[PDB]
Length: 305
Length: 301
Image (cartoon, rainbow over all chains, first blue to last red; front, side):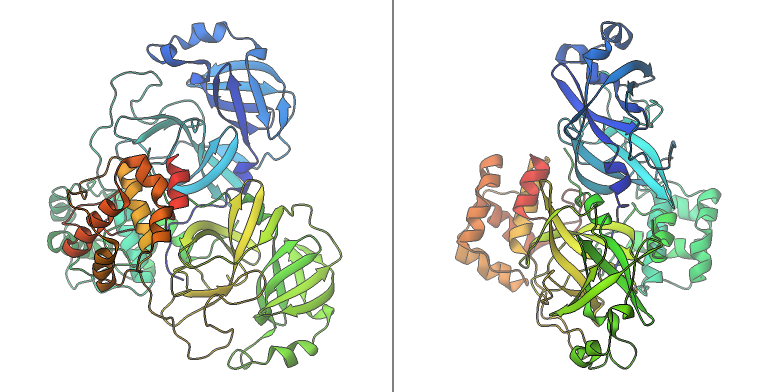
């Protein structure tokens, strides 16, 4: 009954992780029904990445140019096309583990789970958040390309992220399951770099409510603040500016605790200008910004799948 | 690159979670082959929990006394027995989703994944460490009892933990899959409290190498140190004393980074003594110790 950055159960997703190899290039594929999705750069190699003409490289590819391995069974690819940055492979077998699912494009600040895979093999799962600067500070080794990000609603897996690349700063860039990159990032080797990041203020506030819910509330005060004054302070400390929308998304939580959002902003304000003073909140020495308002209700309602 | 506190994929464990009910008590259970494992206290209510006698309690129960369900479907229990603080119930169906598994008793400082369950349904997964005082700093609402901690090596699930209860300080206590409690606790409403919790020195050094490997190394310095001198400081700060066994274990990571273990101890002596100075390591504002050296080498190569 503490509080823990929890990942969704990865069971339904593990069942869709396969291996996709093109010559010497091996990475991960997403097998949903008779389609396998993966990053199109699987048809690349060293030289290729520097200004690749994906269309012309793909033309030189036959269906036999790909080997697809689900466990120890080989999947026969019978069709292939490109959809934006993804390769779509058509296999002769509809994945018997296909879960109820859907594809979504998430928004900056929003969190999800990542099942890290290699050679088609799920190696681990963690939570992370789409950074305001459109990157995930993840943990990926070579051949992790293809690992996916997802959330879960009741029955339905919502796929929202596929991994393509690591930026110079060690941060990470990828696409939604439609092949569109998040951010201005391209799957070429160019001099693209992550712009400056900021703290997801919405998620800090949700976390602060979390603490209060769990009876951890020493930081609350008697005053309130305006949305302006709050944004004048936050942007000094590199926080995303807070919007009336953000305020409304915090609705349920502020209702649950009976603490208004601008009243909670006052608390953040003093936590920023004055720091934490060797105190903790939910056992943390620093403020957390990778819990969304919905994560908090989720974990605090013992929601189940 | 990057460094997250990853759990193992929970898929294999999901397929053995079930709901076990007795009277008006319901908790989770583990379904491997034709046997269901759950905490023996599923047979307690109100009175019982304050100083019970699980021996007299069980004799008064039949197979019929246990409602077991994989999802909406009831499983016929054709047998029951007590094993230490566990209850074992034989069922008439084998579990097809039963994976390659084994029961292991881990040691404080080691890490595992927990699959938090309610009514036999998964809520989430997370990685943690078995504390030196034998508790785990978990996230377990009411009814999570019977959820399991595990590790996965290859195809094979190693179960090491089944959750039994929560202590006054809001931390958690449980048993290996053989029914024996980690640490001196009992499944009774009593005045038991957790011993002194210390930082897991070995894990912290591992995590400092994880920070070096990932480019974060402002905390490094010219000095080195002796084992004795490091322990004299580290103990001042409620840190586990460090041993040669511990240093040896750290070999591979020192050989990876260049940095000698003892040099890293000297860096760690500075951190303990000076605080972090408003800076972070791998984004963290406090030293992190739920990573084993085996954990770090694996995630970092």
